[PDB]
Image (spheres, coloured by chain):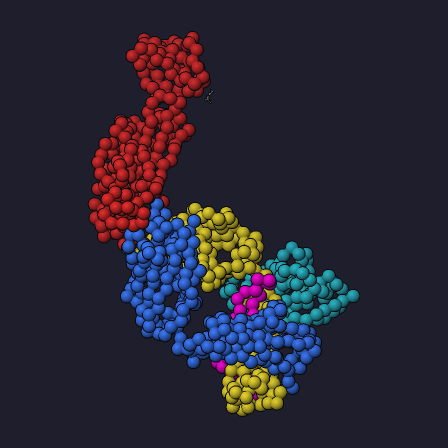
Chain colours: A red, B yellow, C cyan, D blue
């Protein structure tokens, strides 16, 4: 079961190993677009959190699922932020959701009082007000039920066939990270020019025992110009200084 | 068109595990539900997704299967399970339901209380006669036949079986012959002989003209 | 419907058994299994023994230790035993039945006659 | 919170049209969807049609189109059902249930159900029953028990047959509804009582038919 484009589902993924290979190697994923990240590199990265949003929409309507797009969905049902980093995965669902003159459970909002904000979600289905006349019950021009169903008929073409979509939103700052990929750790090397990959931060330099008092809530240290001056090991939590060879 | 077949009647005692399946000709995309219902009453929905129970039903009820097959299961029967259950398909618009499997609380067999009574003068003076044969507190199958004038006759009585008794899981078959006063006075003896899944012999009970 | 009749007796000494000599009529009882069950006051029917077509004797439950070896001779539609006559503990009422599934071992019974017994 | 209530029972002639509806109580008429499903005596549930009051979309089963028509409104907040040219086989109970597949990723199942509307088709009309007692012979006594009978025929359809003003319930054997060739129904109740009571203790059988608002009480008497 997948939710409608309005009142879409949201699942938080944290504290686990993300094996994106089993996700990419799926056949029915006919559309797989990522922003700010390449699918081949997902297995080597680590994020601070992951949010999976799922819903069903028309076929060509999937073009509205992208940063800064315009349209019914992108404006009143589900809007992605301009700085979105993640992936949008879609696959056909005619064998699952389509019914001849049926499948009313999938709906979308046609109009709204104002444009929906990024990652917003309006659970209520109150009737839009027309203004020129009082509207307490059902009414005409502007006071129609805001939701209307797709009614996925198998006779419809690809332009109106049901497509199942799930958007993977990744937060990619450097705060406590917990969704790293299947990469394997390696014994630490100190006092030698070594290439390091600390919880996703990749660089080169010599690692030395730190002498600065990191507070228990801090995980990284920076000099002028965002230069990472220190880092704490995600395994033994010891603070290490980074100096260019 | 899409159809299904539940596989029809069951009997189980409190505590045991029972399983039922509703086959189909084409793979249902996990769009199958199961209802609880007393015969001839508003059903109650138990399973709507193949692996998700609704609010209010205990975990005692369960189900499994996917695609072109499914299996409804009760991990343990209880006296509240005296009812029929219906497998429902909702993969397409032309909604259809199953025939309905019925599970009966199982209390072991018992011998029937067999009886008879001839018609009264109130029935006789109206130009007709009637004789009621009885089977009380006994599984469900049984048969009644008549041997008026010592010869075999059949196809002249109404057989009706009662729903299961919740006190001892027994049944009751009440039957009645109905013929004319001419047919009543024609034969020198009217006799009912009762057959039953458990009985020593055809239980013979008869009367004569006067009595 | 099918007919099932009862025969037995022959009390020689209190050895401990029940002289089942069930019989049938009006059906090819070779197509079905013949079983027998007991009924104690306030007790449900318990599977005691069954005369299967395997021909290796009887299949019985642990409740009867060594006192029942039911067998059949379908050419005469009758059951036969080899054990002693009776004892007080086995005086509980008995019932003889056939299994209505074709060659199956599951219990779905149609039973016949029976009588009472007693011994010192 | 949502709950449904249906109309009462109905009885009409074959070939006519029968009208039945169900109130869309609870929640709102806009957030509700109704669907009608048939259940015939001796058969499981069977679909009739679906209607979404707010969307106005409706459909029928491939064997009841035209024969069945569905309508709904908001001023009354109910789904209207009309069955035309009804056969004699159309004697059945119709249900009105909630269609969950209408909103928010639910599916085509029925979470809320109404009571039920019984529609019967016969040539007879609503009239009282005909009742008469039994008359067993003394030698019918067996094992300390004796039977007592009370029969009802030519009635039109619940008939409550009670013994000892309903004070007796042990051993009650009752008929299911059986119809005769004359378009009339019949029901009989027979009870098992101590044999020594027959003739010594007084027993009476009573009958009631609510549709016609009538009662009948009769005394049973042996004869030899
Ligand atoms: C991770 O595992 C290594 C080796 O098993 C161990 O030395 C280290 O303390 C562990 N770190 C945490 C945070 O569990």
From the image, give the main secondary structure of the stretch colored magenta.
Answer: loop
Q: Nearer the viewer, residue B190 or D48?
A: D48
Considering every residue shown, the one lying at the far right of the view is: C120
Residue D86 location (% of width, % of height): 34, 71
Residue D28 location (% of width, % of height): 37, 50
**In this picture, which residue range is highlighted in magenta?**
B147-172
Query: How many discs appear?
Result: 0
Residue at point 55%, 77% (across, down): D216
Is residue B152 within the magenta segment? yes
Residue at point 65%, 86% (across, down): D224
- The image quarter containing residue C86 is bottom right
Query: Is D108 rendered above or below residue B167?
Result: above
Query: Is B55 rendered above or below residue A189?
Result: below
Query: Is C17 rendered above or below residue B191?
Result: above
Residue D169 location (% of width, % of height): 61, 68
Q: Nearer the viewer, residue C32 or B148?
A: B148
């Amino acid at each position: 079961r997948f939710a409608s484009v309005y009142a879409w589902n949201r699942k938080r993924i944290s504290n686990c190993v993300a094996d994106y290979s089993v996700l990419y190697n799926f056949a029915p994923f006919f559309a797989f677009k990522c922003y700010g990240v390449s699918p081949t590199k997902l297995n080597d990265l680590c994020f601070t959190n992951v949010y999976a949003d799922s819903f069903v929409i028309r076929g060509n309507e999937v073009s509205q699922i992208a940063p800064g797009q315009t349209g019914n969905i992108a404006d009143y049902n589900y809007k992605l932020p301009d700085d979105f980093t993640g992936c949008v995965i879609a696959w056909n669902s005619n064998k699952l959701d389509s019914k001849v003159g049926g499948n009313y459970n999938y709906l979308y909002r046609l109009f709204r009082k104002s444009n929906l904000k990024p990652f917003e979600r309006d659970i209520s289905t109150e009737i839009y007000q027309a203004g020129n006349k009082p509207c307490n019950g059902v009414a005409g021009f502007n006071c129609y039920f805001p939701l209307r169903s797709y009614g996925f008929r198998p006779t419809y073409g690809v332009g109106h066939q049901p497509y199942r979509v799930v958007v993977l939103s990744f937060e990619l700052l450097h705060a406590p990270a917990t969704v790293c990929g299947p990469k394997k750790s390696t014994n630490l090397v100190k006092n030698k020019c070594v290439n390091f990959n600390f919880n996703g931060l990749t660089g080169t330099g010599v690692l030395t025992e730190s002498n600065k008092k990191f507070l228990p809530f801090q995980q990284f240290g920076r000099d002028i110009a965002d230069t990472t001056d220190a880092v704490r090991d995600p395994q033994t939590l010891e603070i290490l200084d980074i100096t260019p060879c | 068109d899409i159809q299904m077949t539940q596989s029809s009647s069951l009997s189980a005692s409190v505590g045991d595990r029972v399983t039922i399946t509703c086959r189909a000709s084409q793979g249902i995309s996990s769009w199958l539900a199961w209802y609880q219902q007393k015969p001839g009453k508003a059903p109650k929905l138990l399973i709507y997704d193949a692996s998700n129970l609704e609010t209010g039903v205990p975990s005692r009820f369960s189900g499994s299967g996917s695609g072109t097959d499914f299996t409804f299961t009760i991990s343990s029967l209880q006296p509240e399970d005296i009812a029929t259950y219906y497998c429902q398909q909702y993969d397409n618009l032309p909604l259809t339901f199953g025939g309905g499997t019925k599970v009966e609380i199982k209390r072991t067999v018992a011998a029937p209380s067999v009886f008879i009574f001839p018609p009264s003068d109130e029935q006789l003076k109206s130009g007709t006669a009637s004789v009621v044969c009885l089977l009380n507190n006994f599984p469900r199958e049984a048969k009644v036949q008549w041997k008026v004038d010592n010869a075999l006759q059949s196809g002249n009585s109404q057989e009706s079986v009662t729903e299961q008794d919740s006190k001892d899981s027994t049944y009751s078959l009440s039957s009645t012959l109905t013929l004319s006063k001419a047919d009543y006075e024609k034969h020198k003896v009217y006799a009912c002989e009762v057959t039953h899944q458990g009985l020593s012999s055809p239980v013979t009970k008869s009367f004569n003209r006067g009595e | 419907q099918v007919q099932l009749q009862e025969s037995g007796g022959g009390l020689v000494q209190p050895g401990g058994s029940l002289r089942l000599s069930c019989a049938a009529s009006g059906r090819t009882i070779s197509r079905y299994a013949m079983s027998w069950f007991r009924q104690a006051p306030g007790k449900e029917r318990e599977f005691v023994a069954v005369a299967r077509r395997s021909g290796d004797g009887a299949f019985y439950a642990d409740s009867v230790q060594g006192r029942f070896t039911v067998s059949r001779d379908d050419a005469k539609n009758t059951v036969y035993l080899q054990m002693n006559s009776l004892k007080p503990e086995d005086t509980a009422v008995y019932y003889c039945a056939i299994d209505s599934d074709t060659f199956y071992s599951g219990s779905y019974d149609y039973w016949g006659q029976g009588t009472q017994v007693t011994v010192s | 919170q949502v709950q449904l209530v249906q109309s009462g029972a109905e009885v009409k002639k074959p070939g006519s049209s029968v009208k039945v509806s169900c109130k869309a109580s609870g929640g709102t008429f806009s957030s509700y969807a109704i669907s009608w499903v048939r259940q015939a005596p001796g058969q499981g549930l069977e679909w009739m049609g679906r209607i979404i009051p707010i969307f106005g979309t409706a459909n029928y089963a491939q064997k009841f189109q035209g024969r069945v028509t569905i309508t709904a409104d908001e001023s009354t907040s109910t789904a209207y059902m009309e069955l035309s040219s009804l056969r004699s086989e159309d004697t059945a109970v119709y249900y009105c249930a909630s269609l969950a597949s209408y909103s928010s990723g639910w599916e085509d199942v029925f979470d809320i159900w109404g009571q039920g509307t019984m529609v019967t088709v016969s040539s007879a009309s609503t009239k009282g029953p005909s009742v008469f007692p039994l008359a067993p012979s003394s030698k019918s006594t067996s094992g300390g028990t004796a039977a007592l009978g009370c029969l009802v025929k030519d009635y039109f359809e619940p008939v409550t047959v009670s013994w000892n003003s309903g004070a007796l319930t042990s051993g009650v054997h009752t008929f299911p509804a059986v119809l005769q060739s004359s378009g009339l129904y019949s029901l009989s109740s027979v009870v098992t009582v101590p044999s020594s009571s027959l003739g010594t203790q007084t027993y009476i059988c009573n009958v009631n038919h609510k549709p016609s608002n009538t009662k009948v009480d009769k005394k049973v008497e042996p004869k030899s």
